[PDB]
Image (cartoon, rainbow over all chains, first blue to last red):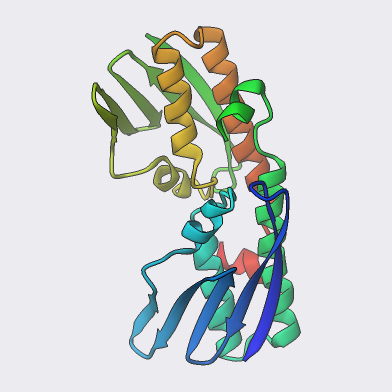
Length: 118
Length: 118
């Protein structure tokens, strides 16, 4: 297990929240607070994800990242898993995803109309 | 009935692609080239959307917008529909959404690792 701690700014709480990524050969888990989602690897199929999604836990914090975000986490994990990325590198690459998510949040439309809505 | 032309930057075509938003009282349409998706207003329920999402058609331009983007379009339309926004207002509010999408694209992770993926 290598653990990656990601700082995601949550407009809901007005602070950065820690999303914890647990990487294993057999599975990956992503938790924020009491919720945990999971992907489990399989030889001849794409990873099996828990019913709960990354968008689920993030939208809960008023974070609205691109739909591909969860798939990025999966890609980072699958590449780390075959040894293409070492521990510090998968950490760096995932931090880039978190940075992107935070930039998306930072750049949200800022008119009266949009501020009132989300 | 009014039409808003939005300019979305596409790394796939190296240019801003024109997304045409048609607002009518009973429905809204969004066109990109030959592709059109549609949301239909219903009196007692949320609008009925195409199953092909705005995100899906943008993914085809190699654009990965926040997942809430389609919902933002819906909001502007519904507000315009009941006259909470005039034609110029709905235009600017939607342009701020396009502007946000463009910022997201511009800020996409650009490490060699991520570029190989998307």
